[PDB]
C-alpha cells in the first residue's frame, strides 16, 4: 500500500504469459525484412480461421495521407518505407506513425495487408525464406493461444516508428459517447460483491471513462499487460480514452484479502474481448486491485495469463 512499484508484487502466484514479451524481444532482434515477412506469414495463416474487424472510419481518415504516400511510391521505396518503420528509423513517416494511437497503427497495417494481398503494394518477395532466428520466432507464435498470438502482433505493430520528444502530438480516434444507462449490462463475479470492482468493470464495459476515473486515488495507477504502471488520473484517463474503447470484460470469479493499513487486495480472473476480434478471441485475464480504506483504486494491474490453467479453480 506504500508505493505503486511495490504494489506490482501483489498476488505473486499469478503466472502471467511472459512468453509474449519474450517472443517480442526475440522478434525485435530480427532483420527488418524478416520482421515484415514473419508478420505477413503469421497474418495470412491466422486469417484462415480468424477475421480481423475492419478499422473504423475515423481511424482510416487519420491514416489516409500516410497510406496514400506509400501507395504512390515505387515498389523498392514501398519496401524501404516498411523497413524504416520496422527498424524504428527517424523519418517523417516514422514520426507520423509514432504519433498514432495503437488502433490507428493497426488500421494502417490492416490496409497495407489488404493492398499487399491485392498486389498494389510491394508484397513480400515470392518464395521468401525466413532467417533461422525468424523461423523459430514464428513457430513459437503459432504454438501460442490465439489471445497471446494477437497480443504479440499488436505489440509488434505498436513498437514500430520513431518517437522524437516527450510532449509530441498524440493522435487518437474520437471518443465514443458512453452507453445509455438503460441498456447497460452488469457483471456478476463469483465471490466478489466489492462495489469498486463491480463499478470498474461495468463502467469500462459502458465506455464511461469519466465515471471510471473517479474510482481511482489521485496518485493511483493502472498497469496494462506487460507495460509499466500508468500513474495518476490524467494519464490513466488519457489511456482509457485513446486505447480502451469498445472492450468487453467478462470477469468470472475472484478472491478478496486484507492488505497493510486497512487496504484490500482483490484478484479477479475471467476473459476479455477486443473489438478487433469480437467473440472469436477470448483472452484469459487477471485483474489485481489494491483498494484504499475508502474503496478507491490505488493500483490495478491487468495480466494476460499463461494458460487457462491460471484461471481461478479451473
Ligand atoms: C504489421 C504487418 C502486417 C499487418 C499486421 C496486422 C494487420 C495486425 C493486426 C493485429 C491486430 C488487429 C491485433 C489486435 C490486438 C488486440 C488486443 C491484444 C487487445 C487487447 C486488449 C486488452 C487485453 C485490454 C484489456 C484492458 C482491461 C481488461 C482493463 O481492465 C483495463 C484496460 C485494458 C486495456 C488494460 C502485414 C500483414 C501487412 C505484414 C507486414 C507487417 O509488419
Ligand atoms: Cl482493443
Image (spheres, rainbow, N blue to C red):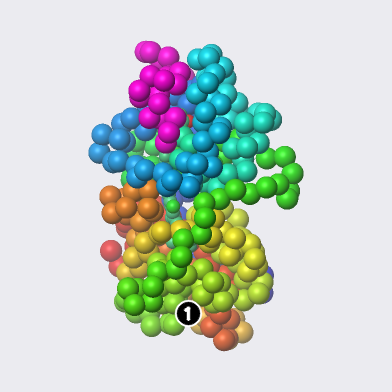
Q: Is mark 1 within 8 Å of ligand 1?
A: no
Say which residue label 1 marks.
Answer: 196
Q: Which residues are magenta?
A: 110-135
Q: Position of residue 68 (x, y in %)?
A: 52, 28
Which quadrant of the figure contains the C terminus?
A: bottom left
Q: Does residue 176 appear to the left or right of 309 in the view shown?
A: right
Above or below for 194 versus 65 = below
Residue in the foreground of this view, choosing between 253 and 105: 105
Vertical side of 208 occupied by 246: above or below: above
Q: Secondary structure at mark 1?
A: helix
Residue drawn at the location 41% of the way across and 59% of the way down: 246
Q: Position of residue 301 (x, y in %)?
A: 52, 64
What is the crowding at mark 1: few (fewer than 14 residues within 10 Å), some, or many (at least 20)?
some
Q: Residue furthest left?
A: 49
Q: Position of residue 122 (x, y in %)?
A: 45, 18
Q: Residue at x 48, y 58 (%)?
A: 244
Q: Is residue 118 magenta?
A: yes
Residue 286 in the image: state x and y as whole percent. 42, 63
Write down the quadrant of residue 137 in the picture: top left
Q: Residue at x 48, y 47 (%)?
A: 58
The residue located at (32%, 69%) in the rendering is 252
Task: Classify 224 as above or below 210.
Answer: above
* Quadrant the N terminus occupies: bottom right
Question: Does residue 169 appear in the picture of this structure?
Answer: yes
Q: How many marks?
A: 1
Q: Is residue 204 visible?
A: no
| Quadrant of residue 32 within the rendered picture | top right
Amino acid at each position: 500500500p506504500f508505493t505503486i512499484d511495490s504494489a506490482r508484487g501483489i498476488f505473486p502466484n499469478t503466472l502471467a504469459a511472459d512468453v509474449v514479451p519474450a517472443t517480442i524481444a526475440r522478434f525485435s532482434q530480427l532483420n527488418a525484412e524478416d520482421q515484415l515477412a514473419l508478420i505477413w506469414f503469421a497474418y495470412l495463416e491466422m486469417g484462415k480461421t480468424l477475421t480481423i474487424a475492419a478499422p473504423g472510419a475515423a481511424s482510416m481518415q487519420l491514416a489516409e495521407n500516410a497510406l496514400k504516400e506509400i501507395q504512390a511510391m515505387g515498389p523498392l521505396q514501398q519496401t524501404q518505407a516498411m523497413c524504416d518503420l520496422a527498424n524504428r528509423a527517424d523519418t517523417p513517416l516514422c514520426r507520423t506513425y509514432a504519433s498514432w494511437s495503437p488502433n490507428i497503427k493497426l488500421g494502417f497495417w490492416y490496409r497495407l495487408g489488404e493492398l499487399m494481398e491485392q498486389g498494389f503494394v510491394a508484397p513480400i518477395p515470392a518464395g521468401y525464406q525466413l532467417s533461422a532466428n525468424a523461423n523459430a520466432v514464428l513457430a513459437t507464435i503459432q504454438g501460442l493461444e490465439s489471445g497471446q498470438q494477437i497480443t504479440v502482433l499488436r505489440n509488434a505493430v505498436v513498437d514500430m516508428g520513431f518517437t522524437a520528444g516527450k510532449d509530441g502530438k498524440r493522435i487518437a480516434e474520437p471518443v465514443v459517447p458512453p452507453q445509455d444507462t438503460a441498456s447497460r449490462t452488469k457483471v456478476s463475479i463469483e465471490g466478489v460483491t466489492n462495489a469498486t470492482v463491480l463499478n470498474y468493470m461495468d463502467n469500462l464495459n459502458a465506455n464511461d471513462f469519466d465515471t471510471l476515473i473517479e474510482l481511482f486515488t489521485s496518485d493511483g495507477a493502472l498497469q496494462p499487460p506487460f507495460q509499466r504502471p500508468i500513474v495518476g488520473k490524467e494519464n490513466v484517463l488519457r489511456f482509457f480514452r485513446e486505447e480502451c474503447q469498445n472492450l468487453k470484460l467478462i470477469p468470472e470469479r475472484g478472491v478478496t484479502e486484507p492488505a497493510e493499513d486497512g487496504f484490500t487486495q482483490i484478484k479477479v480472473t475471467g476473459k476479455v474481448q477486443t473489438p478487433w476480434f469480437g467473440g472469436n478471441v477470448g483472452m484469459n485475464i487477471a485483474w489485481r486491485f489494491l483498494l484504499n480504506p475508502e474503496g478507491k483504486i490505488f493500483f490495478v494491474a491487468i495480466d494476460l495469463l499463461a494458460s487457462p490453467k491460471e484461471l481461478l479453480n479451473f
